[PDB]
Length: 8
Image 1 (cartoon, one colour):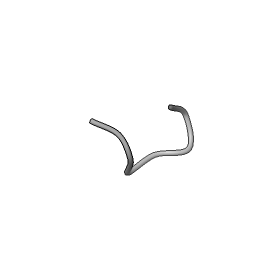
Image 2: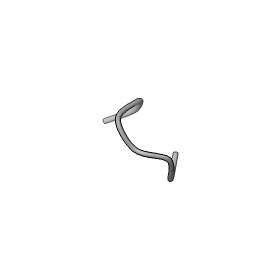
Image 3: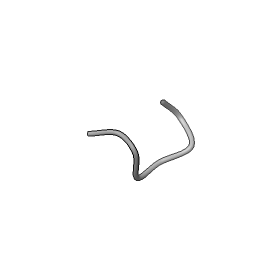
């Protein structure tokens, strides 16, 4: 579920 959010 990466990318898409800054928490990877």
